Amino acid sequence: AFSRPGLPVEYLQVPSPSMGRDIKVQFQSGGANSPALYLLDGLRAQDDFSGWDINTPAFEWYDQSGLSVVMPVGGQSSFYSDWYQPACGKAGCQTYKWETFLTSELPGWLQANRHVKPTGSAVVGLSMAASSALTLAIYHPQQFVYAGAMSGLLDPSQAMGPTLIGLAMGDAGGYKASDMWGPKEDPAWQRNDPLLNVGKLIANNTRVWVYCGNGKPSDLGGNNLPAKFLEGFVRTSNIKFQDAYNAGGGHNGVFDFPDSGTHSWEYWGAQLNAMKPDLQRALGATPN
Image 1 (cartoon, rainbow, N blue to C red):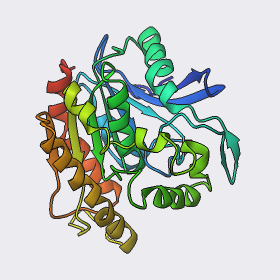
Image 2 (cartoon, rainbow, N blue to C red):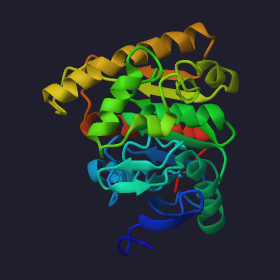
Image 3 (tube, rainbow, N blue to C red):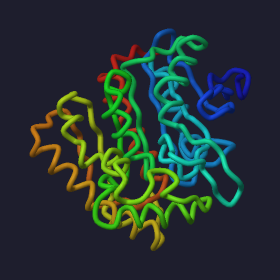
């Protein structure tokens, strides 16, 4: 259903057999059989709207770009992954099988009901979703030939990442990290660690766009200690990723590590706008 008359933005109820419920999805067609752009939300994803629409002119920017914008809604602290145990937070439990939903249910449903090409898509995520995007492309290269990672912890299985992710998950809905990928030594951790699986991005020649601020705010804003420290903190993993990608022979990446930016939406939005033309070219978009 369209949100308003005269505008292309739609709100959808896409059924998810794996999660036993309907997942809300904001959508905007880029035309029949047009490539898809999946925008993943951050750690504190709400159930009403995607952080992308709440905080950015995304839909408006991509209107007529030839790309179909797909914004799933919900999944706080989900990391868009398929969890071992039910996702139990302060507000009860739910089934989290986001990798399944994103790699089969949603694609299929969009192809059949909105004529969205199921392969040759881009998946861009920020914060939590940042590594999710890289990971999705790594295990589903035919579907996602392009992955965008903004301000993410790219080596989640390393150093204190497991503990830090747990602290984050606990503060955002009160979820438990072990319910998702189990204890730190469980194979799930190094499987969902992009820095450790960079070789696949290189082998598959996936178009990679990684972004991360240095912690110093600019005129764009986001000037507060938490936003500054987080950005500075996750930047390290981003550099390690760039070095691994380069060392490994990667030759289809873009690394934007400016001398500014914090962990806030003003920066992620500006970045999503900056990558529009690159996205169109790589996905073969046809304007209008």
